[PDB]
Amino acid sequence: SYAFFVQTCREEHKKKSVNFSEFSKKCSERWK
DNA sequence: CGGGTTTTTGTCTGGCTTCACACTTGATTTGCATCACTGTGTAAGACAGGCCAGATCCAG
Image 1: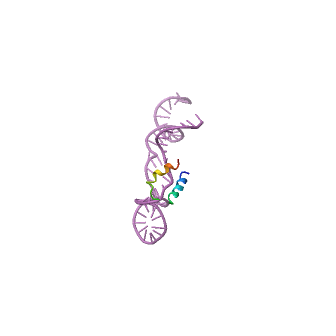
Image 2 (image 1 turned 120 degrees about the vertical axis):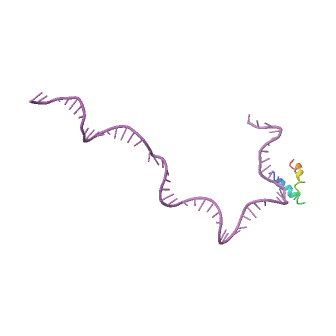
């Protein structure tokens, strides 16, 4: 379940995918 | 009988290696079965039997 919501958010903010470094601090304000 | 606080880990995430993987055929190299033999078995003791010797007995 920890990956489903992340994949949905990835589709979300990717429909608007090679930058994993600047994505580190994105999930901090999502699961909270 | 189960609340705190670090360990112990598989991932999420997508993008970079170094090895993995279809075909030949003619060798070339290993692996394994087969066959006629080998050594270690290895010195004394028990018992019957013929043979004289000498003791055991016989009779004038």
